[PDB]
Each structure stands twice: as structure tokens, then as C-alpha cells.
Image (cartoon, rainbow, N blue to C red; front, side):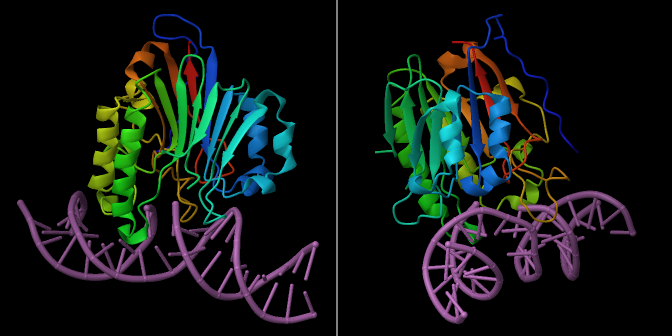
Length: 270
DNA sequence: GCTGATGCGGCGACGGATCC
DNA sequence: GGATCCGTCGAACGCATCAGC
């Protein structure tokens, strides 16, 4: 079954207008994504803040098109030192953040503090084929939760990006045949449930659309999975509970091409 | 400098068994 | 004997290194 994201809801449940638009995109190769016109899509989306994951690009190789985004002029990039062509994340913002830091105290995490909230974008480590990196993922999950818990102690938190797990069976097309697969192990799902519990956080999209199936943000390049919408929901906006009144909508931009992930977009009334 | 090989890291199609 | 359940396997991508010119 194909999926059609509902129209953008730009007013909070109470009736306040959205003032902040955040777009998160796992671009799977920033340079390839730019050549596949992904930045033309960003310009049409016109977000206040853009978070990118899996850029696979060091700062000295960023294409000059990125210096031509005047409404996203404050840019922060993080790549691994060891493995240049892998991982990597970026955060672009219309306004300067108050503070920016990297890591969770790998080029996987950027933390940016704004006036009324802290934003984290993450490329969560994949468990690997054959689950060869699942134990590392479990240790990483626990270190990440502890780091996030110790941030939400100040302002509310928005966490976005590729969290590399489909939380529940509704979050992927083939839950039964993938329960031993990276992204849908009981270990990764439980780690997600624990993140929501411990910090605490809510899944923005699931909060608004608790029963909507076939909503995915990732499709393997092979076996024409995307045209069949055989996909996984791996990309999220998770919010502190104190931000749920401010939540207008959480979108999945199914039609935007240029990666094996599609963009996601958050509308907040702050 | 440039190309294209190879290497590495991000599962759905399918073939076979079991169940009523 | 259709539905379901399970383990096996081939392959689209992006980017790195490397050879060769």
C-alpha cells in the first residue's frame, strides 16, 4: 500500500500558529544528494533549521552550493576522524544558536541550544548485517540516553535524525521477516522504548498519528522497494513532553528524492 | 587529474517446512 | 493445500583506496 502524508497542520491543537519549521534529512552522501538536486528541495521546504545525517563528507569537501543558502547561514558540521567517507552530520540554522557542541561527551551527534529549546540531531550507529555491531549499538544507546537525560534537565529537548530503529511493527512493512535484522531487533526496539521513558520523550509523529500504517522514511535502493513502499520508519522527531502543546505537525516528505531516506519536517508553535 | 576496479557498509525475494 | 513461518542469498547505492596512464 502506498502512503500519502496528510496536509501540513500549521496550528497547534489549541489554535496557536507554527513559528518554527525543522527539516531533518538522512542524505546518504551529501555530495551525491546535492547532485541529485536535494538542495533544490530544501529551498522549496524553506525550513528555519535543517539537520542532515550520513553526509559522508568532511568539511573541506562541502560543495560551494552550501555557501549559497542565505536563510541557513549558520552551519555546523561533524565527521568522524578515523573513517572519512562514513557517517557525518550537519546542522544549518537561519538564526545563530546560543551554544553548539559535538558528540555525546564519531561525527554522529550535534547539540545546539536555542532560546526556548535544545536541539540534538543524531546518526545512530547501525547494528550491521548479521547483527555484528548490535552489542556496540546497545552500549551506544545507553550512553546516549544518559547523555540526553542530562540535557533535558534545563530546557525542553527536540531530538531528530536517523535513529536506525523501527520502533514498532507498524513502523516497517515487513516486521515478521526482519525481527533478526538491524533496525528491528528486540534489543534496538527496547532501547528506543527506554529512550522515550528515561529522558522522557514523545514520538511526535506517532503522537499525532498513533494508528497510521505504511508511513516510512527509508526504502532500500534494491528490489524497487521505494515504488512498492516497502519501507521502514527510521527518522523521527522526539520531543520533551512540555513541547507537545507546541506541536503542530510532524511530516514525512515521501516524494522528495535524492537519498534512500526521505526528509521529515516538524512544525512548532513557540 | 581522471577513470574504473575493488572493498566496505547501509533486507526483500525466494525456497522450503509446518500447520490445520 | 493456502497461509504462515523460517533461514538463505544477491545486489543498488555512495564513497574510499588503489593501479594505471
